[PDB]
Amino acid sequence: LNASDRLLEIMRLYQKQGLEMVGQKLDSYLADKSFWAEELQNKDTDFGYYQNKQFLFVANKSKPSLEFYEIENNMLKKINSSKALVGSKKGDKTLEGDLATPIGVYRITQKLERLDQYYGVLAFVTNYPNLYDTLKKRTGHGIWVHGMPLNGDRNELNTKGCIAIENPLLSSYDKVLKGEKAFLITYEDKFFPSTKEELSMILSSLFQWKEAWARGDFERYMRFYNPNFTRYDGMKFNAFKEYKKRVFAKNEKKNIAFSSINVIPYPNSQNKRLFYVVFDQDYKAYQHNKLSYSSNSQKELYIEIENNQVSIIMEK
Amino acid sequence: LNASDRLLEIMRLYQKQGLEMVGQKLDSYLADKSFWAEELQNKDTDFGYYQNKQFLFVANKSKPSLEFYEIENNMLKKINSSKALVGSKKGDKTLEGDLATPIGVYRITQKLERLDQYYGVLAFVTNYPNLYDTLKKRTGHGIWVHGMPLNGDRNELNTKGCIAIENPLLSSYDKVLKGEKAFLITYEDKFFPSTKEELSMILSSLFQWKEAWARGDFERYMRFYNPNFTRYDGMKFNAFKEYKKRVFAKNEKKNIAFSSINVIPYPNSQNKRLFYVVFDQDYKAYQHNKLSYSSNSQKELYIEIENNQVSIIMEK
């Protein structure tokens, strides 16, 4: 079953039964692993799935090195790479002042340009501690990707956790970036890419979870949640399930849509198969066919694949 | 590839902008000649485009003969053919009692069975005079496809305009038809088939016209109409245009959907490239977001292609 068959089937449905049945068919594709497997088959998927154009930094703490990529239609283009300086402590960053460069997936939130000359041309600010770090109660702050001292001093072999590279290369990255946000994937010894099978399982599950949510299927929705689940505000599984039971019993109608979806393999010290999933969510709920609630938000999930099953370990 | 890209566009649109925008995108394909060119490329298109399953008699006045077809996904299955008795007058039927079998595209409206023995096992009633005949002021009635005398008489060489075939075969067609309406194409010496280019032009135009109508684009809508236009109720081009300018100035919201579209080459004296278009139409209009008018009707168009341009010459 291929893309041409699916297009023909969409149009046949549209001409014969109209628009509502088209939506139901499109939903069935989105919930279908094989549909994603086909879309992904010739794409560069090692660093994840990215719907829109994005920029990716990849840091190897061990070498140490930093690479920079552009990703468009899920095809990678390597811009450059170099050696880097990183923190002195091996493994996870878990505490303020532990001198460790964090392992995981981070976002570059801003550029700083009026800094001590030690930081070089600029500093890209990472969002350590990210949601995952925050729900694990890891402490610390101020992890940046920056340059080398402007005076030309080279008197350190390690930072206190920041990632530092040469200024000309750093400037060249900034010119490619043009003020766009970047992801940063940082790993330690060896990187374990997301496979096409894993991305296919996550994306199909993602849409199944959405539609179980929207239609108020409490049992199906709850099965996507890992027993260890933690919500962004600290709520754990039992209270979460209690609450959702009540909410779902109200049987309100909802429409939910996910866009700008990225799914990114998440390096971690236990080498669990973890992924960070981030997307825009359009959410609408109705009471007696009157719109009673709407929101547009940025959602974040952390998902594990274990025992060949997808589960949600954290959600904002 | 293209089908991969086209599908991806639809899937992204569905989640980013909604099912309504998906419908508009499918509509843009239906308005595109190259879309139809591709869609028709391996279809049996000589007798026209038939969206759903349909049945077709083809009568050659000159032979004389009658063929019967089943048409499913626009592939012809020929059920049978045989010799036939037809009217003695060559050329057009224009008048009550002129003994001519009419030339053009007709519809079988009903089956009669309580007949005089002369007429055989049954009569399929054709709709002579059709809309075209009627707007051309042609008169007469009772043009049937029927059998041979039940008392075994086989005297006559010609009917008074009906089409007569052997009773065993006629019953066979009836059992295949099973109460369904059928089309009849009748032509005189040589049949000049609808081509794939003609059909693709007519179909893309049909959907362009629908969009111009529904979105209220007066100038683009009026461009499809031939100067010689006659509406089913006699109204001519200038009065039609005047009335439409008024209606379009109201800028009412309108939703229009077509289904079971058939486009059938229309044989004619002058061998002009004329076609009969017939479809079901669901029409709704609104006033300040409230439904003010709805209808479900069978629409009929007669269309000429001349100097590579599609025009409407008659509409019901």
Image: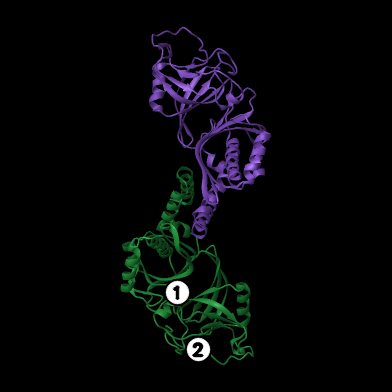
Chain colours: A green, B purple
Could you tell which of marks 2 and 1 lies nearer the N-terminus? Answer: 2
**B65 versus B290 height, above or below:** above
Q: Residues within 10 Å of mark 2 (few under 14, many from 20)?
A: some
Q: Quadrant of residue B124?
A: top left
Q: CA distance from mark 2 to mark 1?
A: 23 Å
- Relative to B219, B31 lies left or right: left
Can you give x and y, in whole percent of width and height, for residue A269 in the image? Answer: 39, 79
Q: Residues within 10 Å of mark 1 (few under 14, many from 20)?
A: some
The structure residue drawn at horizontal position 54% and vertical position 77%, both measured from the top left corner, is: A109
Q: Quadrant of the N terminus of chain B?
A: bottom right
User: Between B147 and B141, which is closer to the camera in this rendering?
Assistant: B141
Can you give x and y, in whole percent of width and height, for residue B239 in the image? Answer: 66, 34
Give the chain letter at badge 2: A
Query: Is residue B293 something that shows in the picture?
Result: yes
Circle number at residue A160? 2
The structure residue drawn at horizontal position 44% and vertical position 89%, both measured from the top left corner, is: A98
User: Between A178 and B99, which is closer to the camera in this rendering?
Assistant: B99
Which numbered disc, 2 or 1, marks the residue closer to the eye? 2
Q: Quadrant of residue B121?
A: top left
User: Between B205 and A152, which is closer to the camera in this rendering?
Assistant: B205
Q: Quadrant of residue A122?
A: bottom right
Give the chain letter at badge 1: A
Can you give x and y, in whole percent of width and height, for residue B266 in the image? Answer: 58, 28
User: Between A176 and B258, which is closer to the camera in this rendering?
Assistant: B258
Circle number at residue B161? none
Which element is circle 1 on? loop
Specify the amino acid type for callout 1. Phe
Specify the amino acid type for callout 2. Lys
- Relative to B147, B32 lies left or right: right
Which element is circle 2 on? loop
Circle number at residue A191? 1
